[PDB]
Amino acid sequence: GRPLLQAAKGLAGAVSELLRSAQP
Amino acid sequence: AMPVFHTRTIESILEPVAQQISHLVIMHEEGEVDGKAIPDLTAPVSAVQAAVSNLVRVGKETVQTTEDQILKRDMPPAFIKVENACTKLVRAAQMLQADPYSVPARDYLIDGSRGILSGTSDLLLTFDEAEVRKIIRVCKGILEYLTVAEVVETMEDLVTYTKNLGPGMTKMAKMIDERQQELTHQEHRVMLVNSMNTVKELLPVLISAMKIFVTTKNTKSQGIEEALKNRNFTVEKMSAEINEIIRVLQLTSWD
Image (tube, rainbow over the protein chains, first blue to last red):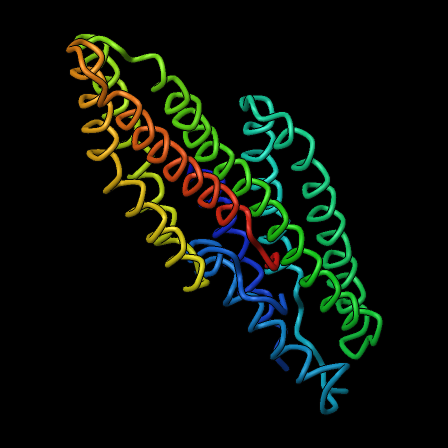
C-alpha cells in the first residue's frame, strides 16, 4: 500500500525543489 | 494546510511542502517585494509534471484494484485537482521564460503549489479513510461475534468460540495499536489505547463468565440466573468500548 505513498513523497519532493528554485 | 496533518505519515510527506509554500508567500506577492527576476523554472516544473503523472498512474492502479467503492469515487477528483494545479505551474514557467518579473507567473506559482498540496492531501486522506474502514470492519466483525456468545451452552462449543475469538481480538488489538501510533492527536491516541485495554482485559472475564455459565447449565441447582447477568454485562461493556473505538477512529479536523 506504500507505492501510492512513495509516489506522493516523490511529488512532494519535486514541488519542494521547485519552490527552492523559484527563490530570487 | 492550516490544520495539523491527520497522521505522522501524511505529516512527514506534506509538512515540508506546506512550510515551503508559506516561505514563498512571505517572500512574494503576499510578502515583501520581489520585483526581482525569478530564474527559469522550466526544468523544475517539468520534474513536477513527471511526479504528477507518476502519482496519478499509481493512483489509478489503486482505483481499479480496490474493493472500496468510496475509494473508487473519491480518488479521481484528486487526480483532477493535482493535474489542474500542475497546468498552472507549467503556465508559470512559460510566462517566466518570457518575463522573469511576470506577476501572473508568481500568483500561478503560489496557486499551483497550493493546488498540488491540496490535491495530494485529499488523495492521501481518501486512502487513509479507506485504510480506517478496514479496521472498522474488523471491529464490527468482533461485535457481531460477541453477539453469538449467548448461544454457547456446551463445554466444547465454548472451546470453539474461544478458538475464533482469540485470533480476532489479536488482529484488532494489533490494528489499533499500530493505528493509534500514527495519530497526531494525543487525546485520540489515549482514547483508543484505554478502550482497547478495557476490551483486552475483559476478554478473560468474558471467557470465564461463559464457562461458569456452561458448567452451571450442565450441573443442577440455580446459580444460572446470575451466571447469565455477568456474561451479558461483559458482552455489553466490550461492545460499548469497541463502538467507542470505531467512533474515535473516524474523528478528524481534516488536515
